[PDB]
Amino acid sequence: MSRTIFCTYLQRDAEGQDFQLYPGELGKRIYNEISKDAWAQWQHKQTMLINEKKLNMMNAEHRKLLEQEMVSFLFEGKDVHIEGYTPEDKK
Image 1 (cartoon, helix red, strand yellow):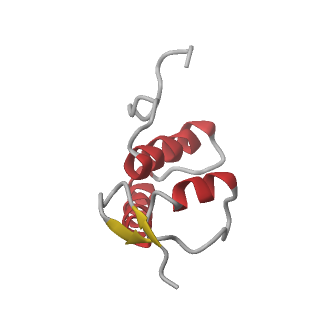
Image 2: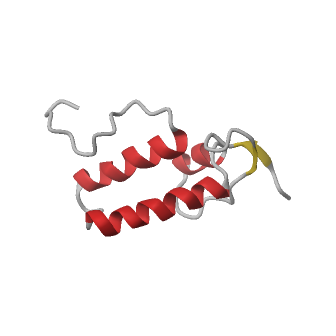
């Protein structure tokens, strides 16, 4: 059963994502806007980025990196500046 949705990254009819295979609230909030296509696209790119950045997910620095880029690429309409690391104390 291919459920048709409108993916932000495609701006057209797309097939909805599968189910909660790890996330929950964020998962479904993204699944309804993101097709399997875009989901695969980004996760490939970020995996590549992680190989370049050599970052670990145990640090808020690199953890918020993932968050910034992920939301900006998939959801697009984020409120956070994509500067990677924030040199300002007040965020």
